[PDB]
Length: 6
Image (cartoon, rainbow, N blue to C red; front, side, top):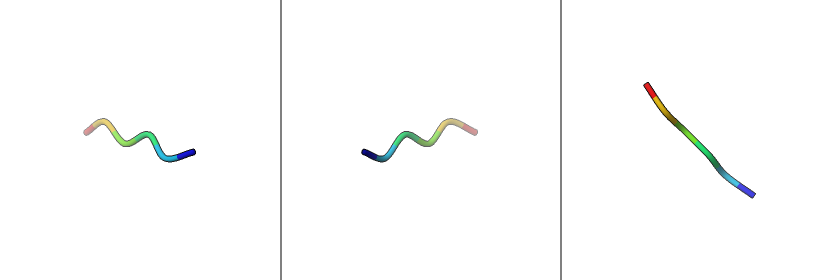
């Protein structure tokens, strides 16, 4: 579902 990489 959610994958965030900053």
